[PDB]
Amino acid sequence: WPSAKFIDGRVAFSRMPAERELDEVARDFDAVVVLVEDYELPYSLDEWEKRGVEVLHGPIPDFTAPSVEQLLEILRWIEERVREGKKVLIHCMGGLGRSGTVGVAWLMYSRGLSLREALMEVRRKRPGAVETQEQMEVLKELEERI
Image (cartoon, rainbow, N blue to C red; front, side, top):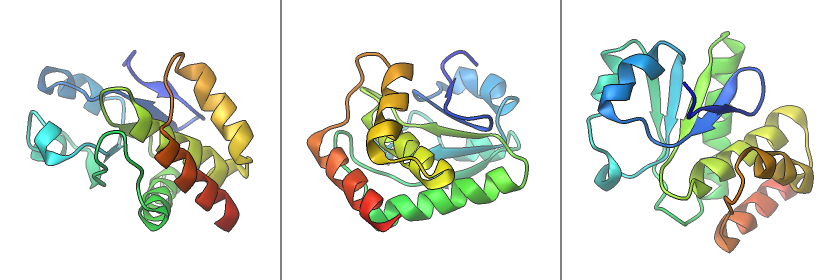
């Protein structure tokens, strides 16, 4: 699925799949982290279940940061699926800052990367995408705990 950009061998991030795209995406991933809010969702997250995909719904408002504890819980969940041999998709929508934040966090969490190097790696895979200052702050908090 070309919207998905992989950040390691098993974890990717992307924009939101449309409902017509679900059959395709569901054959490429085993689990999905949904970071959009319910007022951004054009379908029920049931549609993933009906296609054999397990879901973690961790809503974050657009342009804002998750809490650091919310971040760590999402990271632990991704790690669980990865350890099971599964491929995981992190998606948000819009400017992509929310999935960008979680993807940078994942590189710090799983590979031990510093924040500044994790930011550089995600930055190159998404030309023109930025994290807001609020998202930068929680990532710094994550670095200070990790």
